[PDB]
Length: 229
Image (cartoon, rainbow, N blue to C red):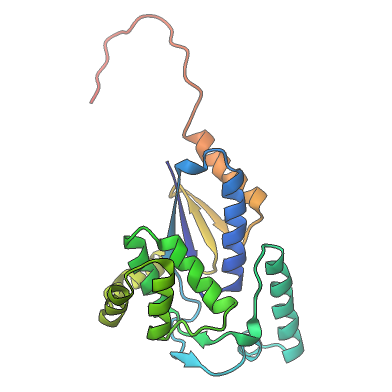
């Protein structure tokens, strides 16, 4: 097996682009059935208020200290880039929500083996559908659409069951020196930073697989005294 640990935020347009680019690489990878993908929580703004009422453009402009026009240029670039991945962004509709509860929902989903589908649904909800991913009703609905037990998902969110696990994911990232997302870890050994091209990720997958499958040796001589486990 090859394990791929991916750190990502729901509020992260480059993370969604990166998810698609990774999926393209994985589709090209002959041993894709041997790959285990695990999503890990990362918050770009863990101190974000529950819901920040301003436009994403203005939020971005404040974050990077730039003009509304250049902030718009940035949004436009990301929109155009995402369109090449089949993604239709609607930044004008984005609700600037704290994503802590959404990350908790992905943790809930992953216990049911639906981590990726939940991650995917939340990215779409955030980037394309103008949904508030801090809103409990909204999260419950999205859980239902993914095929989860909507009532159980809601209860887990209200109890904060996966809160610690999310914070641990975030601490893990800090310890690994991960300061920007999306970030890929392969085989617990190799780091790949940002929304890399499919070719790069496919190359990494292939490199790791090859490393774990050396050519069999040609044995010489007879077995001599040896010790084993």
